[PDB]
Structure formats: structure tokens, C-alpha cells
Length: 303
Length: 303
Ligand SMILES: Cc1cc2nc3c(=O)[nH]c(=O)nc-3n(C[C@H](O)[C@H](O)[C@H](O)COP(=O)(O)OP(=O)(O)OC[C@H]3O[C@@H](n4cnc5c(N)ncnc54)[C@H](O)[C@@H]3O)c2cc1C
Ligand SMILES: Cc1cc2nc3c(=O)[nH]c(=O)nc-3n(C[C@H](O)[C@H](O)[C@H](O)COP(=O)(O)OP(=O)(O)OC[C@H]3O[C@@H](n4cnc5c(N)ncnc54)[C@H](O)[C@@H]3O)c2cc1C
Ligand SMILES: NC(=O)c1ccc[n+]([C@@H]2O[C@H](COP(=O)([O-])OP(=O)(O)OC[C@H]3O[C@@H](n4cnc5c(N)ncnc54)[C@H](OP(=O)(O)O)[C@@H]3O)[C@@H](O)[C@H]2O)c1
Ligand SMILES: NC(=O)c1ccc[n+]([C@@H]2O[C@H](COP(=O)([O-])OP(=O)(O)OC[C@H]3O[C@@H](n4cnc5c(N)ncnc54)[C@H](OP(=O)(O)O)[C@@H]3O)[C@@H](O)[C@H]2O)c1
Image 1 (cartoon, each protein chain N blue to C red):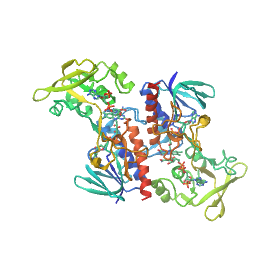
Image 2: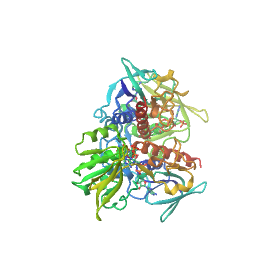
Image 3: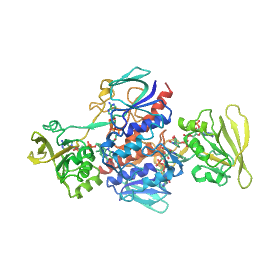
Image 4: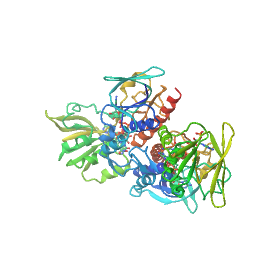
């Protein structure tokens, strides 16, 4: 009944859907939340070719805008599973079932947790995984950011609009982030560093975070310091629960594809951050997306 | 002396250069003409995520704009060869030589010729490979477009702004172009079709094209019809002469890479239309580009 169903309307899925529709495939794009995925949790995007800078949510809007006019069927759905029935597949949401000849999985990735005490307890209360969502709640605080990669360092620079200071805690003596972002963090006066450290505990009164305990990973020295907010940016986990049974994920849960975005399962493709890969960006999400769209077109042509 | 040299400033090369520079690689971007590559020969771009529609040359400008500010070294150069010297490489232009630790080849593809009589003769004179360049020269003419793929059909729709009529000649009974583009050509009143045919000869007086002779590929019937212009869009050839000796091309001249954009030759990567692949688009040029940039960064880190 559908030629293609695409799960997830971040930039990879939205690009796929734009292509399947231009190919006049009967196209359903399922999204559990707001179109844009992670781009909506991004303050400022500087490295998407075509725009010198653009707010995450504006880029999200621009990419979603033409889909309806192309005849993409945009629907709300949280997908809970996928059943393969050889010459077709069933996708199960909370309420519905959807029959399709092919699937492009574009469900991305989610924040990795610290799994330390106080992290859950203070979830609503000074612990955040999204600077653009929560930063203004921490005006004039001492903010802590945990992590050393592009999200930690970039989101720390953003958080300097709000905090008295922002401190980046990284578990080595060298950041992983892009040099230009590093260099911008080195130079920014409101950014402090706690190198070679990991957090051990988040502590607070009954209402909110007050301090963090942390350990130096070369000496074992333990320190506790006061902070009003903690943003955690220590990497990503796949968002692929609905396919765990299917034999298409690696040991860590990422979807395995070949270079044409194909899983084991004919007619089931995956794109973007959810795939097992190293280089997660909007550019590679968009490319993966277009590639999947084309492979699905071909797959459906042969069916 | 360079960490990376990128040859070609179309969207693939310009994306690569934006990434190498953000990685603070000492970056040279060589281009023989105007930044934008094929996008400059494109009238209207509708399928680049982020823009609902945008003129080829405007998208070119936007992608070129931030490169200087990132510290990309933008230079004029036509590259004639590349010499590998193990731990470095030499790139030869017409006038200069450039030493670099890595190369990202992003030189794209060029129009395939018909190789029929009158095609060279009337080159300046009613034969064109670029509708956006020459279309207005053919106001009120009967225009012919040869080809059945996305460029023929899309450039024919554009040419309808200028011609009395535009006729698409395709060598089968089914277009290769995207269905949406087909459907738009079917519906457009100024677009005629000559199906199942190939052109045999382009004829003219001393000053210009007047007619085309063509053959039906199922019956052998030969017909000659009057036209004032002919646009030829019958596919692409690689632009990779400077590496022919190097053992990195297939029998047709396309550069062979793996999925991380690597050739045989360590430190020599290729991206975009110049690679051996099937799916040539701005989205996949941009993705390939970002991927190469990252692989080059890593390659140079290990050197
Ligand atoms: C703070 C931050 C800043 C970033 N900045 C940049 C940047 O500047 N440049 C850059 O190139 N990259 C950036 N990235 C990375 C980039 O945003 C991602 O690589 C990209 O968004 C991946 O797109 P995707 O479509 O694969 O996944 P996502 O954007 O993660 O989209 C996945 C979508 O699937 C939906 N979903 C998940 N599960 C289900 C389900 N079961 N059913 C229905 N829907 C589901 C989600 O709601 C989501 O909308 C940044 C990331 C972060 C966190
Ligand atoms: C008419 C037309 C319309 C199109 N429309 C679309 C569209 O709507 N959407 C879409 O996604 N795709 C479209 N495409 C395809 C798209 O433009 C290409 O896939 C894309 O431009 C490839 O980019 P690239 O950087 O790999 O190569 P190119 O854009 O071809 O750039 C290669 C660059 O290398 C330079 N160069 C070549 N040799 C040398 C040398 N020896 N030394 C120095 N410089 C050199 C050239 O000057 C050129 O600037 C279209 C193509 C055409 C012809
Ligand atoms: N502008 C952009 O292009 C942009 C922006 C944001 C994200 N992204 C991309 O998105 C993907 C994910 O980015 P990310 O930064 O969220 O994740 P990431 O690249 O996995 O980096 C997470 C960082 O946190 C560190 N870390 C892990 N556990 C830690 C702990 N317990 N304490 C302190 N530090 C810890 C890691 O250490 P190690 O480094 O030692 O492993 C790493 O530096 C990447 O591919 C990234 O490039 C891109
Ligand atoms: N909007 C876009 O996304 C866009 C726009 C333009 C180009 N592109 C991409 O650019 C790449 C190249 O596009 P293209 O259209 O230039 O080339 P193409 O896809 O190779 O198509 C060339 C077309 O011309 C036909 N042909 C070849 N020789 C012929 C002859 N002698 N007489 C009549 N017809 C002949 C081919 O026939 P067969 O079909 O029988 O082989 C084919 O249909 C493609 O990957 C394309 O998708 C994309």
C-alpha cells in the first residue's frame, strides 16, 4: 500500500522523502515529534553548505517546508516495531499499522547518559542534555558541560550567552571537537576547562543541583565543585529499538548498512546518524538520505 | 607545505574545503573557472534540502562565500597532473607546482558529445550544451533537446521560456528523468517528444544550424526536421585527465574509491561526480565532500 515509509523526519529522512516523492513513490514520512530531529536542538549551524549560519530550527523548517507540496504524506507516529513479510513489511506504531514495500529508517541517535548518581534525580532540576532548550534557565549560573566533542564544545560556546561561566570537563587533555571550535573555546573568556576528568556524582538539595564530584583520570584526585547547571554531551546512542529482533544492528545497536544504505533485509534501508558509522553530520545525513531514496526507488521498481 | 589540496570548487570541493579548513588544515582550493561547477550551468535547483528553489549561480555563491573567512586559500589553477612522491604529492598546473600531503579530487564531469556530423561545425552556431548559458539566443526558435535524463528534461522545461517549442528526442520510449520532471514535461504544452530516436546529423547553411536528421531505433526510419537550436544532454564523461597514468580510474575514466572516498593511493581521495558512481547530485556531492575532508584530516594526522 506504501511504496516507501520513512521513519524519522530529521535531515536524513526529510531528504529521502523529498527524493522518493520526486520519484512519485507513494511516500509516508513518520515522525514522533517535530521535524528537524537534532537540528532543532542546535543553536547555530555554520557548516551546512548553502548557509553561512542558520539557527537549527530555521534550517528544520526550510527542509520540511516543501514536503507536503511534493505529496509526501506527513504523519505523526512513534514506531514500536517492524515486521518483515517478504514481499512487504509492516510498521507498527502505538496506534496504527502500515503496510509498505520498503522502509527507510532515519531515526537518528540520542544522548548517552553518564549513569552516575544524581543524574536522574536532578533531571528536571539542573541536569540537561540540550543547551538550546534549557540554557536561558541558567542565567548568571556557573554552568558545567561534560564532554570534549563537537557538541560539548559548541554548546558550551552557546551557553556563554547565559552563564557567568561555562566549564568544559573532558576526560582527556585534548578535545575531539573541530579545531576551529576548540580555538574558539580556548579564546573565549567565559570558558574554563577541567581537563583529564570525569564526573562521579551530581549533588543537590531537594530542589536542585548544587555541586559535582569528579575524578582526575591520571591521578585519581577527587574534587567537588559548585555548579548551578550541568549539560552532558558525552556521545550518542542509536535510536533503533523497533528493529532489535531483526538481525540488522551491531553489538552497540547501530544499524549496519552497505554503501548503498542497504541492511540484510531487502527493502529495508537505513540512513544518517542511526547507521553504524563515525562521521555524523547534516551533510552526510542528507547524502545518505538521497542515496537510500534512490536505492528504494530501484528496489520497488524491481518488485 | 599544504595539508590538503582540493581540485575543483563545485559543491563537492567547496564542502570539502569548508571541512578541512574548520579542521584547521592548511588548505588550497584550486579552480579553473568560476566556483559552483555544474550548479552554475543549472537554471533552477529544487531538490537541495534547505532551499525550496534557488538559481544555480546563487547557490554557488552561497557555498563559496564563507570559504575565504575560514582561511581556505582560493586560487585559480587548471591542473594538468599529479605526481605521487610517497610522503607527499605534487600537483602541476599550467604555471605552478604545489606540494601537499593529501589531495581531494573534485573535478566533476563534463558533457558527453554526440560525435555526429555538424556537431563541431555548428558549436558556436546553434549547438549548445548549456541551456542557462545560451537559451535566450534562441528566442522564438524551435529548439531541440537530445537526451532523456534529468538534464535533458529539466533543461527542456527551462528552455520553454524562450522557444516557440522545445522538442525532446530520446532514444527509448521511457524517460530516465525523475517522474516529477517527466510529468511536468508531459503536461507542458510547449514540449514535444520524438521518442525512440537518435540524431544522425546536424545540418546548417554556413552561418547556422537549420535541421537535424534522425533515426528511429526500432524501425530504422530516417527523418529530417527543421530546428534553430540543439541542446545536447546525453550524459557525462569524467574530468580526470591529470590522473590517467596513476592507476586510479576505471576503463571509462571515472575515479574508483571506496566508501570513505579513498583511491589506491594513500592521501589521494576523490569526491562527487568524478567518482565512479551512479547517483550524481548536489546532495551526494556535498556528502562525499564532507567524508573526504574527514578522511584527509585523519590521514594527515597519522603522517
Ligand atoms: C547540539 C548539536 C549540534 C549539532 N550541530 C551540527 C552542525 O552544526 N552541523 C552538522 O552537520 N551536524 C550537527 N549535529 C549533528 C546533526 O544534527 C545530525 O548528524 C543530524 O541531525 C542527523 O540527522 P538524522 O536525520 O540521521 O537523525 P536526527 O536528526 O536525529 O532525526 C531523527 C528523527 O527520528 C525521530 N524518531 C526517533 N525514533 C523514532 C520512532 N521510533 N518513530 C518516529 N520517529 C522517531 C526523532 O524524533 C528525530 O526527529 C549536531 C548535533 C547536536 C546534538
Ligand atoms: C543542467 C544541470 C542541472 C542540474 N541540476 C541539479 C539539481 O537540480 N540537483 C542536483 O542535486 N543536481 C543537479 N545537477 C548535478 C549536480 O550539479 C552535480 O552532481 C554536482 O554539481 C557535482 O558537483 P562536483 O563538485 O562533484 O562537480 P562539479 O560541480 O562538476 O565541479 C567540478 C569543478 O572542477 C573544475 N575543474 C575541472 N577540472 C579541473 C582542473 N583540471 N583544474 C581545476 N579545476 C577543474 C570545474 O571548473 C568545476 O568547477 C545538475 C547538472 C546539470 C548539468
Ligand atoms: N558542527 C558539527 O559538525 C557537529 C556538532 C555537534 C555534533 N556533531 C557530530 O555529532 C556526533 C556526536 O557528537 P558528540 O560531541 O555529541 O559526541 P562524541 O563525538 O562521541 O564526543 C563525546 C565526547 O565526550 C567525551 N566523553 C565521553 N564520556 C565522557 C565522560 N564520562 N566524561 C568526560 N568526557 C566524556 C568523549 O571522550 P573521547 O573524546 O575521549 O572519546 C568525547 O570527546 C559526532 O560525529 C560529531 O562530529 C557535529
Ligand atoms: N535534478 C537533478 O537532480 C538533476 C538534474 C540534472 C542532472 N542530474 C544528475 O546528473 C547525472 C547526469 O544527468 P544527465 O541527464 O545529464 O545524464 P544521464 O542520466 O546519463 O542521461 C542521459 C540520457 O540521454 C540518453 N541518451 C544517450 N545517448 C543518446 C542519444 N544518442 N540520443 C538520444 N538520447 C540519448 C540516455 O539514454 P538511456 O536513458 O537509454 O541511457 C539518457 O536517458 C544523473 O546522475 C542525473 O540524475 C540530476
